[PDB]
Amino acid sequence: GTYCIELGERCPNPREGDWCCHKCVPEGKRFYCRDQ
């Protein structure tokens, strides 16, 4: 892993904590680790 979930991958609800550590952001119906 790259310290956190890599950019572009799916993430669980960010309320549980951003393991995306860019941003775990809702993209439609899912959450993704995006730079947004």
Image (cartoon, rainbow, N blue to C red):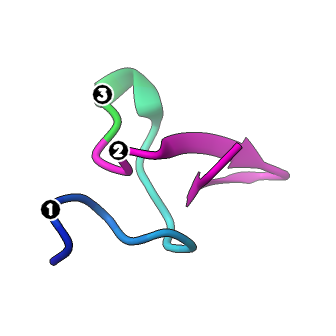
Q: Quickly name the residue at label 2.
A: 21
CB-based contact (under 8 Å), mark 2 and mark 1: yes
Of the two numbered discs 2 and 3 in the rendering, the one whose residue sits closer to the viewer: 2
| Residue 34 % position (x, y) | 61, 55
Magenta stretch bounds: 19-36
Q: How many residues crowd around disc 1 within 10 Å: few (fewer than 14), some, or many (20 or more)?
A: few
Image vertical order of residue 2 relative to residue 34, above or below = below
| Residue 13 % position (x, y) | 46, 37
Q: Secondary structure at mark 3?
A: helix
Q: Quickly name the residue at label 3.
A: 16
Q: Quickly name the residue at label 1.
A: 3
For the residues marked 2 and 3, what is the alpha-carbon distance in whole angstroms? 12 Å
Q: What residue do we see at 38% from left, 71% from top? A: 6
Three-letter code for the amino acid on which mark 3 is drawn: Glu
For the residues marked 1 and 3, what is the alpha-carbon distance in whole angstroms? 17 Å
The quarter of the image holding the N terminus is bottom left
